Image (cartoon, grey):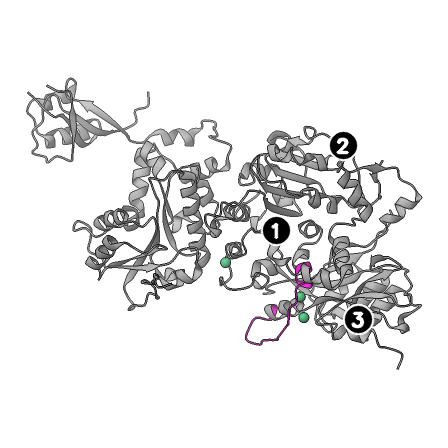
Amino acid sequence: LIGTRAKYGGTLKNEKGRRHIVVCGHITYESVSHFLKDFLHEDREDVDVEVVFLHRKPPDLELEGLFKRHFTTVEFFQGTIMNPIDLQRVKVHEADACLVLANKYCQDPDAEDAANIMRVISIKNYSDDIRVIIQLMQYHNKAYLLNIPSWDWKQGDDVICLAELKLG
Amino acid sequence: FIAQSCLAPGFSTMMANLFAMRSFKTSPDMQSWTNDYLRGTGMEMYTETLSPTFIGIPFAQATELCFSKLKLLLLAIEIKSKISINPRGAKIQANTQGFFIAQSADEVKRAWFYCKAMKYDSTGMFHWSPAKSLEDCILDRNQAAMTVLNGHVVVCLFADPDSPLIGLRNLVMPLRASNFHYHELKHVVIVGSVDYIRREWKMLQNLPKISVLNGSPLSRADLRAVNVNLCDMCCILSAKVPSNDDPTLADKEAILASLNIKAMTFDVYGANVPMITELVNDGNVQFLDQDDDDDPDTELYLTQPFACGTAFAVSVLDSLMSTTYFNQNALTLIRSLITGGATPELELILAEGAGLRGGYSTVESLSNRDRCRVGQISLYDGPLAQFGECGKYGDLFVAALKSYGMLCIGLYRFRDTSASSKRYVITNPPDDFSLLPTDQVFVLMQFDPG
Amino acid sequence: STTYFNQNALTLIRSLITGGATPELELILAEGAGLRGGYSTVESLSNRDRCRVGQISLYDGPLAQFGECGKYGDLFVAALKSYGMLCIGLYRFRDTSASSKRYVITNPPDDFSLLPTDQVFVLMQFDPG
Ligand SMILES: [Ca+2]
Ligand SMILES: [Ca+2]
Ligand SMILES: [Mg+2]
């Protein structure tokens, strides 16, 4: 009974005017550090965009220290995309885009792709007008995303298929 | 429930709400369609003994009197026993048990005190076929295209070759009842793995007009090969065992199939294809529809997809424990209303293991075909169309009952009248309800020989 | 990060490594009938006129004279004007004094000194015939 704790929670509340994005999917220490190094780089044009992470597992000690070093730019919340309550907390309807990271080193690529596709359905269910960028392990699963009525490549929706790009 | 929805869309929602104890409280701070729908959910199913004043008069005069004077809907009676649903020319006898639809058991008390002040099976209740083989029904893309399937029923099945068997027989027989003429039967096309359908073909040999297509319902080529745009109802069924890894991942295929068809276009609209999807998880109903606000704590019967009849689950059938215990005849009425008529003799014949057994048509068997059936009518055209021009529900109920012997149960009305082609279910609207020309009526229609 | 900051960036990569995959090809393949052929017409044959990725060697040819201790900028201008070739980088021997291993130099300066054994990444136009 005493060995429990709820460290992360609460809704995202900040000022108006600035823009932010939501990152979900495979959130580990090296998944965030590699993403943040490329996202926040000197060569990139200086634009103030906030990065919000949403994962159902509590981060370990090393990941929490990484968030502290990016306190003014990176924030973390505990929750899942499939829950509409958690979607409102991180303010999905006002974010520029939602980025879904895939577990490249997965035993079953079919299982990983199916879970990622369901996240896009949940995101589009909350709001039809939202940019979604997703990693797909296999090309034949790209057909399912294209069949979504709210999916629209002309509006910024993009699919980055690792299998197509790697063999290309 | 799914099979009856093919004959009348939205019927599963009305049946599910009729056997769940719900207290209805009016609320002004919500949409009018929501208030109208919630009024129907308050209706339940009750049994009461008819007053001695009703003795002698036929059923048609009896149910009309209850609707007008007593504001109660009488749809079935017990004859010395047997249960008959909307019987024509059936005089009310002494101590006759009546089946009523009302807000509460206090309302039906008014019905007790009142005064002036081989073509078919052995039972002859289902159509029969001379045990056609599976290979004679398997269809390919090339030969399914040349076949013109109009007004048919498409069964989208997700099942592995070793998936646990589901009662596909329980889905086809209600569509093959003898109460339907052979020309008005609906062709059934099952899209799925024959390695699974082969295990269940034993119970489907003697059912006419059944087609099988090897493939996947998620493929647009297979759906176009069976003319999903022309079908009367598309059923998405999943027989695969849940992996229990995550409840939100239990209905990935069912949700994807629904979204796939909804976005298809034909040379005409994918969203116009009538579909009903059974959900393993109640919480996955939020993904079925996009133009609604999803709340994870809301009851399933309160959700928009369920109110429109496009969603179903087994979690709405727990209340049948209480319903059956308090009245055994209540369960008999449900089975005789959704299965197309399954007498206890049919139980022993099927339990032997030889499958459905046919019988030679005689005088006593053909009399069994004369029973009421579930259907829908539209006020667009016909003699009853003049009631849709801002008429009253009570006026339509009386006229239809006297002329065609039709019993109106509820309405299937557009959610928005100013749009989306989505219709919700209103169960037993008041006699003062205002009708619309676009409304559809759930009716119990008598059998017409010829 | 590349796709988020610019959607056109991902489109350029896909059109450069997949040989050209237009959004119409996405829907045809997603149906499930496989690759579908088409009868050659006037409008289709115009699609074949696009640049492609290839390599050239300074061992022999009109461009071989730039490999004799020449400059990368001189090779870039001459190839662009004559054959319409765009030089992206060099594929040069790791050791020039051995092992047959070559590394990649991306966008060398115009003052870069070339070698007769160097190979050039180029974007070559379509020549009908
Ligand atoms: Ca009630
Ligand atoms: Ca929804
Ligand atoms: Mg109820």
Give a yes or no on whether discs 2 and 1 share a subunit: yes
Please tell me whether mark 2 or mark 1 is closer to you in this view. Answer: 2
Please report the residue visible at 20 percent of the width from the left and 29 percent of the height from the top.
Answer: C121
Q: Which residue is mark 2?
A: B131
- Left or right placement of residue B223 versus residue A141 in this view: right
Q: Is residue A6 magenta?
A: no
Whether tag 3 and tag 2 are in contact, CB under 8 A, the answer is no
**Stretch of the chain drawn in magenta:** B15-33
**Depth check, front residue: C26 or A52:** A52
Q: Which mark is residue A125?
A: none
Question: Sequence-wise, which precedes: disc 1 or disc 3?
Answer: 3
Q: Position of residue A43 (x, y in %)?
A: 17, 49
Under circle 3, the secondary element is helix
- The number of numbered discs placed on residues in the rendered structure image is 3
Residue A9 point in image, percent of width and height: 34, 64
Dot 2 beta carbon under 8 Å from ligand 3: no
Q: Main secondary structure of the magenta part?
A: loop
Q: Provide the residue designation for mark 1.
A: B276
Q: Is B291 drawn above or below residue B368 in the view shown?
A: below
Q: Amino acid at mark 2?
A: Ala
Farthest front residue in view: A1
The crowding category of the residue bearing disc 2, from other C-alpha atoms within 10 Å (few below 14, some 14 to 19, many at least 20), is: some
